[PDB]
Amino acid sequence: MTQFEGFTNLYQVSKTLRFELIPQGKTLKHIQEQGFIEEDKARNDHYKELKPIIDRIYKTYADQCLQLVQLDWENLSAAIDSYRKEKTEETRNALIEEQATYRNAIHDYFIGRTDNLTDAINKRHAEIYKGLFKAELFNGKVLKQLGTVTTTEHENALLRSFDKFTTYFSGFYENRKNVFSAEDISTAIPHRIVQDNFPKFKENCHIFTRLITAVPSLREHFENVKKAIGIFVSTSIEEVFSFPFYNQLLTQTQIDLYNQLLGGISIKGLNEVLNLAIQKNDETAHIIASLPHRFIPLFKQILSDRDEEVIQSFCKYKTLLRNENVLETAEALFNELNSIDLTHIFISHKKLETISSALCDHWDTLRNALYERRISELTGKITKSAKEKVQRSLKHEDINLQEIISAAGKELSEAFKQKTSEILSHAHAALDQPLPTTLKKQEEKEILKSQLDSLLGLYHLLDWFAVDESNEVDPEFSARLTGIKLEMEPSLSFYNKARNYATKKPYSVEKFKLNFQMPTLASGWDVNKEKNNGAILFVKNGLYYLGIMPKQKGRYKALSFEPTEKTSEGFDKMYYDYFPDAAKMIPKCSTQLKAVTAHFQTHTTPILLSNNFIEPLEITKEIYDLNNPEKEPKKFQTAYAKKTGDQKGYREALCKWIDFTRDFLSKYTKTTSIDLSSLRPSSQYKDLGEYYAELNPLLYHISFQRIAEKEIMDAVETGKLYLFQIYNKDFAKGHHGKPNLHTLYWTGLFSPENLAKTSIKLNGQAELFYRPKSRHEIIKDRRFTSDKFFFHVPITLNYQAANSPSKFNQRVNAYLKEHPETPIIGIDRGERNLIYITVIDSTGKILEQRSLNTIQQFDYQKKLDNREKERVAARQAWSVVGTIKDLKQGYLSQVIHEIVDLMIHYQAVVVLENLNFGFKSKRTGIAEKAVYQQFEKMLIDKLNCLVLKDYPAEKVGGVLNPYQLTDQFTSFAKMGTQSGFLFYVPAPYTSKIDPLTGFVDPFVWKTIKNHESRKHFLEGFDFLHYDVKTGDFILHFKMNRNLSFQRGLPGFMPAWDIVFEKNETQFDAKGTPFIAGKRIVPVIENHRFTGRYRDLYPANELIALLEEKGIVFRDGSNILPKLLENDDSHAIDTMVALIRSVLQMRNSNAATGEDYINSPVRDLNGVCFDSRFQNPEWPMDADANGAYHIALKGQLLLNHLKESKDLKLQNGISNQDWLAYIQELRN
RNA sequence: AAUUUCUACUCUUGUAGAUGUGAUAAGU
DNA sequence: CTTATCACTAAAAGATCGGAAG
DNA sequence: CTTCCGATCTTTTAGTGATA
């Protein structure tokens, strides 16, 4: 019995609020007089300049330490091979522990505990590892200790400039602890060495050994290219791809040399040699090309290397291009292209579509041309292996121009000669048109973009030829193309820089962190650390103040604020109390002091501690062995239970440690005032983590106390305290609407209900930033014209729960299995509606379908329509592109509220569109997969902690009890099918589909081009007849026919009754007349669509065609043999055109506005479904048709949960299963 | 067209929604 | 342009300065 | 007049659980 309102308080979530600080009183004058802001700006500059020096010393220590490892590597290779062959859990954990011990073994080199080094160098490396992550790297100790590093006097002087202030680097310090650690983190050098580079090197070795087993005739060729490249001259080819040589390959420059050997010098590499071998088309070419024939390069090592401004840069670029005469070289190359041999120069395969998009009319016509011409040149009968050989020989291989000019004819030799005679001419204009004076007028940006794109299209035409010498290419043409390529390669870089400059923003959001000459400013608010951190907050009359007390004449003037009776006028100051993360402080303040470990070496008696204790606390020896053992897993850790299985001694030691913790909690002078009667006794705890997760919320407390106003006023006036007012738009005097969500979090954090029972915790690690001025009347950009102080503070919501969600999917599947009647929301994008919603019931009937064009009754469809018009109205308009892309993000940010409101009201499971396994065209408003990915991520992050503004604080959904329905976001690929209530289903076969019987277009088209193909396609049907009672053409289709021309996705039923409906008038529910069965088809000119749309009436056109042919059909007889006997091309062409028009599900015309669907199949009731009927029980528009089938896919996933005994979904549903399920349920 | 920040407007010197900040790596 | 990491800290420990004593 | 011992400011430091 799990209620939907019980899906709250499951895991903590960390958020961060930001506010603006107004300097109250005359603290602005004090800050300006003392000059903190200029000093902090100079120090931020020094920190930015000092970061690469610390990176340099880390780099040289990493290289020096990695050059000494001689580890042996067969064991992890055996482990990963055992995983590859078995794929069981036992070998999986064996591989995991083998990777862990390899990372530990290589980390022993950094920490200097390696078994295979002597003691002196071990002590040297251990001292270096100790001294890297302390202040000893700043004063100059480890600089002399390393010896290798070279530092000039300026870098050294700015490196010692952080003296007595080193902790400014502290997070950065711990950031570098990510790199050198032995953990499984992706930024670890051991992880990069073991789990990333080594699998690629091992598989490189295996492909090399297998390919040298196949034939050794190219082993000498490998030796010659290794000698000619002059890379790794001290070793042969056989041992450079062996495992022990990886012990020399860990350094970055050796990785670079390995990559240079594999890829060549830009002189051929191994990949180019293999390409030359497989392109020869001898027996060795088939014996190697059927085999794996690639070596993927290794990853780089961590921390390793490899308006007038743009106007002047482009002016110098154009002047240098005019001096080099790149247009003259290009026109000379295009002139000599007309006479040289075309066999010796090749076209890169990556633009095999692109040439089809440029030199001809369709983006894949020349690919089909060369494929069918290779098929026509095949010797013997066509088989599967020969077809696959042809497909392989044309899929990823460069092709010379003679095959292009023979398959596609000589006509391209004119058209190509046309197109270059355009582009270089504009390039000539781009090298003749003068530079614009500024970039503030529209025409200046116009002429600038034209100057970029002509030369950019010239690059994109020069990318056509195969720049890689994978075939036999004469080197002088290669030299000329590469020279003119490298003369003007960076034009893409100036294009990107000009686009991002003209795109970004007109403001300067750059800010630097203020510190007020404090090492640890606003790191914590606790009243014992109130002196050093110097950050407090006051509350008065609903307003919130931040007080920062700086050091006075170089010393912390310990000003004390006195308690005051409440009704006296004054600020309210908190008394923050925290014992941070008791799992790590209870070791810290007991059994890990220097005194206790110094005593426990030479003694066995228990030790009594009486420092910061009200009574002497006793530490016996056994608890010291429990916390500090010989091995890494402690006795009371569950890793000991997993590794050994001795549960009895585990439970006894856990009880002893838990008793010691409970004894400790009552006598430390900070935690003595806390009530611990809320804890269950020691023996009732299953493990240790639950104890710490329940104990941690008990140790944090905020209590307000009244401070006299006069003392604060003289503290501000004197200069001992800097008082700022915390501000956003909700603390203004004219504020009367609903607040922002962060203001709701901030107000609910200091509510009395939260102060009594902590649900939101005010975290430490606050930051103060400063932003310069950035250079009734409503002034544009008021917040961006003045220098401003910002305040960034993190908070932790749902503090009473754990940190990790554990099995969120299991819990939500349990709730969904408990409740079968739960509705399903389906979300789907479309044309003429940006986002479309369909909330359906469990039985399949829709409950509410809507378009999300309108938000606050002032719809965004006209915004996208108008902005997309002005896109065209001024070219592409670099300026407007960004406004469109941000209006899309803002539209999605407003759509988030509508979706979570629908989910909350309907208590439903939402079902989104999976962006993998899918392709979406243009015209869908939001199309870009990155923008919708950002949407799905924003939705997951919003439903991670869902809170509504109008809800009460105490109720579920309020600030003190937010809704948590979705698991924490981790990756765009590790989502799977579900994340809590966020279900994902594959995109296609959801928009163009009959919503009542599930008919889909079974043929694959764009292959109806040859005449006998049309003959076989038309002969595939069973029979066509005419009915005079309804005046319709009934054509019968069997799914076992036209299998070569049908898609390979059979449905449930094999029968279909396609109907050409009488194209008469009809009435909807609203009485608006509409022609029944009419279709919309584009007009085609020069075998290409032109965008203009025309209306088609299939039955009337077929009547006209058949009476013009003189075919008698009023008897109800078959017409297909009555028309195929003449073998007329025009008749079969019109028949195919009418079949395509009839099978066209969607019909839209944005110029006139109508948009509908039309199923050409009679249902079980014999009617033909028309979405222009506007039946509320069926999808209104085509976007509703898409969203309803997305919701039905979610319903299918729900049923897949229901039949399964285990509480887990199936994976992504195959399309054949979806079609079978739909055509089984609906018929 | 006013915003801690973004989007979009002006009955209202503001409105409706969203907003995890800072830092460093790595991939294309 | 994405994917992974870490911090969200008070108290112990040690450097720094100033006063007392031989 | 120099050296040793006590206040003050800065800087390290401890580390729990659980599958995919």
Image: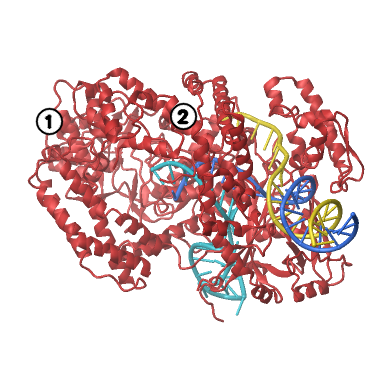
Chain colours: A red, B cyan, C blue, D yellow
Distance in Å between CA atoms under marks 1 and 2: 77 Å
Q: Note whether residue A1217 is visible.
A: no
- Hey, what amino acid is under mark 2? Asn
Given the current orientation, which residue lies at the most extreme left position?
Answer: A339
Q: Are marks 1 and 2 on the same chain?
A: yes
Structural crowding at the residue carrying mark 2, measured as other residues with C-alpha within 10 Å and reported as few (<14), some (14–19) or many (≥20)? some
- Judged left or right of residue A1121, residue A651 is right
The label shown at residue A717 is: none
Residue A994 lies in what quarter of the image? Answer: top left
Q: Is residue A518 above or below residue A128?
A: below
x and y percentages locating residue A916 in the rendered image: 43, 40
x and y percentages locating residue A468 in the rendered image: 25, 40
* Disc number lying in front (1 or 2): 2
Residue at image mark 1: A1125
Residue A277 lies in what quarter of the image? Answer: top left
Residue at image mark 2: A247
- Judged left or right of residue A200, residue A147 is right
Number of callouts: 2
